[PDB]
Image (cartoon, grey):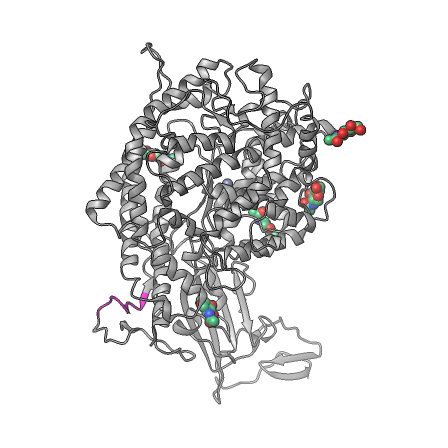
Amino acid sequence: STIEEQAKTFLDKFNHEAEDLFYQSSLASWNYNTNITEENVQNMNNAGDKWSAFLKEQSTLAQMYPLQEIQNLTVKLQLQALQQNGSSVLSEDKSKRLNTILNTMSTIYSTGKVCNPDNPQECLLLEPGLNEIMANSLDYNERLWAWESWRSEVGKQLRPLYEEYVVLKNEMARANHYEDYGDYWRGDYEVNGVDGYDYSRGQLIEDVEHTFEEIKPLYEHLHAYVRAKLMNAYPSYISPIGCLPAHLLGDMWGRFWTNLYSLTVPFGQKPNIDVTDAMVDQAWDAQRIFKEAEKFFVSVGLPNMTQGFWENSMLTDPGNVQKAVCHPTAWDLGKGDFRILMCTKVTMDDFLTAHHEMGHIQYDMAYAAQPFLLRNGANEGFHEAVGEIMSLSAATPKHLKSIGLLSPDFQEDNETEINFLLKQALTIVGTLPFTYMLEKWRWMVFKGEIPKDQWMKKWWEMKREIVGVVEPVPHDETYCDPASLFHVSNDYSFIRYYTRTLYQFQFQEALCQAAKHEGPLHKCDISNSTEAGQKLFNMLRLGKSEPWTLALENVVGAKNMNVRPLLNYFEPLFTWLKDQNKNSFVGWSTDWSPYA
Amino acid sequence: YSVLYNSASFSTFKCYGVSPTKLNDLCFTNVYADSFVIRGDEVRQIAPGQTGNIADYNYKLPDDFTGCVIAWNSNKLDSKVSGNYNYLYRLFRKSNLKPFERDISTEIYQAGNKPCNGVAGFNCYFPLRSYSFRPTYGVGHQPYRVVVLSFELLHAPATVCGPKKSTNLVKNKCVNFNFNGLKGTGVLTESNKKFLPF
Ligand SMILES: *[C@@H]1O[C@H](CO)[C@@H](O)[C@H](O)[C@H]1NC(C)=O
Ligand SMILES: *[C@@H]1O[C@H](CO)[C@@H](O)[C@H](O)[C@H]1NC(C)=O
Ligand SMILES: *[C@@H]1O[C@H](CO)[C@@H](O)[C@H](O)[C@H]1NC(C)=O
Ligand SMILES: *[C@@H]1O[C@H](CO)[C@@H](O)[C@H](O)[C@H]1NC(C)=O
Ligand SMILES: *[C@@H]1O[C@H](CO)[C@@H](O)[C@H](O)[C@H]1NC(C)=O
Ligand SMILES: [Zn+2]
């Protein structure tokens, strides 16, 4: 027989043999993440041995089936995923330093100790330290204090290791012949061999800049808005036209702006929408929240849950002597086993999170008919683009009224809409520029444009001309601000946070026509439209058997990412922002400085 | 055919070629029962004109099959904490099976172009493997006991003909009667003749 059917036989054997092995690992993982104890740690190791070892052997014998002599697309895609080496292309001597640097970075990032100078009595570290304090504090020195201490310790003790890590990752990627580590990560979005759907690895950067340029007026308007509104709480130390400081933008790294609504309220004296009071008065249990999350998916387009999730999933915090780590996640153990790991209180945040988790569960089972190696989302971003749109439909003041939580006699005023839009734009809109700038810095570091010497200077002046952030203290080239980051100290990417941001809005607008809905886009709530659920099913059940561009086009009709839905979400906010920015100049000047 | 039809303890009970009742008092030369255990999702494959591993390389059903099929869950028996590795099933066979044909060989498949020499490896694999049923598995993988019943009729006496219903008898009044296949009409009266024992 020819190589094609032999490869098919090996594929079938692998698909059968991986399932039972993965199930025990998943069971051990659920047991640990539900019940923490010393004796339930060998199982991890035990599982983390067996499965892991098996995996490497299935990459050892899988390279003798060349893809050139196969004419079926799906098995070609399968072989591409399983023919990758990983880190075994590196020799053992050079592989004993990569893992060493990873261990050092993880340990040092987890090990935090921030103390004030000349005061060895009190220290506060990471949590419940830095994040809690410098989000609600109106003291200049206190805000700039932990800001400088964390960078002076972690940056100093991780910059030399970062220098070695960059070149090591470049070498390990070049051993796999992509061009370098940058193309190594940018090849995740690769599709070849399909007409009208193929895509190149280098076009990602330019395509991202295209959607980046079509949001700059909004970013500049909100920049001037927040600067003018923080000129009130902080009387001075702010340029009339310039870069906002790095210690006045919510979190440490400025990547989240949720901590700025306290000082910046569009219309005051008006409480927002709160249904948690209704939840606590008439006393729903921990279940009915999930049952309503269940009945939403039941009603729209999707079948109801199986019996296994209702007797094998922990919903409420156990406390007691049995410890459980609260981290809401969706678990697909295999063999038709689905559960959710989370601890719930009576909160609206848990109400919104339950919809996200249920969407994740219904997404996992959607591609359960696909082979074992095709049981995943189209990329690393579509998976969060499926269950997150539920929070867009679970927060409208029509489904809450329908389920009996929000005051059926309420009148929705012109004042609350802009407040909600600013509140939820401080999270989604306010993180794209910094995140993509960080990714661009990583890409140019890995590609080779910037030598190791002019690293922070370029970083700090991109902090000025792109984000609009000024140094509270002039830093020298001895720190490493990126090294003190969660997904930079530990090996993870940042591109997934950008396309996802545009995916969640692109799909929604499609269903907004399928729901026959009229009104503003933010009020678009899908309900009683089996057609929208049918289209959702027509894209969830495919998975990795088809290119991601095809999956996107099946709903939105576009072979490339578009930003227009995001701005179509923000017409009232844009109008209101330009409504109260007519007395001060918009933009920033990258010449002002707190230190002059 | 009464402890089967009336008892609603069966997930799947379907008769092809005959009705459950009505045709439950017609008889044939022989009855053949095939019993086995499969996974929850394979019970669909047991039908005439079906393709798949179970329908082809394990047991083939003829297109003109006449009989009945019963299939019911057995998760309370064939599920073990350590895994139910006892049940074996086949992947690697050179040709499809004929109806009512079985193969129980353990020949290593010569998938490649070189003799396997009886040892598994590259392009050489074991043909039979196990479910490993677990208590926490879903209905799509939970074990199901399946039995198929086939009726064979030939130029034979066909001596398996079901139960016969009977009614009480009255006397001294002419009626219709069916005495052991003898149809008649009239009065039945006590007698005193001497019939031979046969
Ligand atoms: C959690 O694990 C401990 C082992 O230290 C065990 O004694 C306990 O019964 C477990 N709890 C549950 C709910 O399984
Ligand atoms: C490619 O492989 C899939 C997987 O079994 C199969 O369904 C499909 O028919 C194959 N392609 C062609 C053209 O037969
Ligand atoms: C799911 O929906 C079906 C209706 O098709 C119903 O018969 C079944 O009881 C439902 N199950 C649950 C757990 O709600
Ligand atoms: C139809 O929509 C209303 C309001 O959005 C909702 O209360 C109702 O439950 C929906 N219909 C069904 C069958 O869920
Ligand atoms: C709400 O109505 C008032 C009254 O006309 C109007 O001035 C205001 O602009 C409306 N809200 C928005 C967001 O336009
Ligand atoms: Zn999620």
Q: Establish if A195 lies above or below A31.
A: below
Observer-nearest residue: A378 or B143?
A: A378
Q: Percent x, y for residue A62?
A: 31, 62
Residue at horizontal 49 percent and vertical 27 percent from the top: A469
Observer-nearest residue: A158 or A224?
A: A224
Observer-nearest residue: B142 or A521?
A: A521
| Quadrant of the image occupied by residue A569 | top right
Displayed-image quarter of ligand 4: top right
Extreme-bottom residue of the structure: B155
Q: Does the image show residue A69?
A: yes
Q: Establish if A281 lies above or below A202.
A: above
Residue at horizontal 52 percent and vertical 37 percent from the top: A432
Q: Establish if A472 lies above or below A8.
A: above
Drawn side of residue A89 relative to residue B51, left or right: left
Q: Percent x, y for residue A482?
A: 39, 32
Extreme-left residue of the structure: A93
In the image, the segment drawn in magenta is B119-128
**Residue B120 magenta:** yes
Count numbered badges in the picture: 0
Drawn side of residue A296 relative to residue A123, left or right: right
Residue at horizontal 32 percent and vertical 27 percent from the top: A478
| Quadrant of the image occupied by residue A319 | top left
Q: Percent x, y for residue A364?
A: 49, 50
Observer-nearest residue: A184 or A363?
A: A184
Drawn side of residue A301 relative to residue A478, left or right: right
- Magenta span: predominant SS is loop
| Quadrant of the image occupied by residue A554 | bottom right
